[PDB]
Length: 222
Length: 222
Image (cartoon, rainbow over all chains, first blue to last red; front, side, top):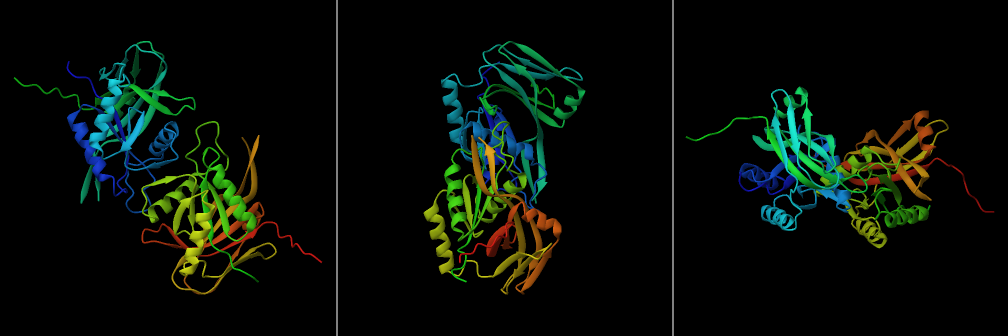
């Protein structure tokens, strides 16, 4: 292969948030490089009546709340990037995010558990490697690229649904998802997050991750 | 009469918020003094599964979002107190809130429009005085005092419903509410807020306010 993925970057943003564009660009650049699992969660607290993006959801906002609690904070803001489900940083701080992810890796707090995903014809197969502890197998479904009327703006990896498909206990496992899931991934893609939780059950460190894009086109040079 | 009410204090808090108790006490003290219209809005972003107060609501959280936008901020936190619908301050900063309200009054940004409320037998009557501009006649219904299991903690003026009952255009007006409203106020009380809105329609400066308690007991000394 080559160099393993550096980590997970979950950006909470909104088209109604004026200071978010810079962070949106940051994420787009990281997704283009493909060295991180990047996700964009549009929050609903920026909607009022006009500039209400059809990409936001209450569920996305609730996830940012889960992180707020787990991180011991007393509030939320946008743009906010959550790294490896372990810490937060300004969404536009590209240098900070990569330096943070590197710091995690150097401490063995990176993506230590192998996670693989692929289409098994009319089903989705998720392969998880061996490790220690317990974690949920979380799947975040997103559209690859979606344009919205401002003119027109483009957003990438906008999550529209998140679901837990099983539990990992340290043992290697394979989870098979039905055609209904295949159809959803085909709308863009999905990210598999092997995520632990704290005592309260809120989202915590992500110890493994993978992205499966709906487009399975193999690009080759001869 | 005597000295007019100093202003409106809207506290966003939650029993799931560990740093909120101090702010809750602050509000209780101001409500006891009765020189301000005090309201407590329990937010829902501190609920997870256990310490989920039955006093929180999505609507309350949305109101804090409305204020976030109007105030030009990019996030929310608890405990947060909104003063006269014009600015925010730490919920526990008792000195700051009163000094802020005083600063508003000295600038003629206090409660300049008279607002009165009373029970008309089986109906609720709200009397609004003359002024300039446009504002919604907002009614926030609350329980006077509610205890929740931690032991047991007590919360005051916990808002459980907010509704606009009419529009003020600067002209003196009287709004009559049905028996259904009387029943709700009797569950605790209500606060009438003559509130303006910004260009986006979000909650802005409150130019008049009044509280009507369900208990209409007249205390006299002879």
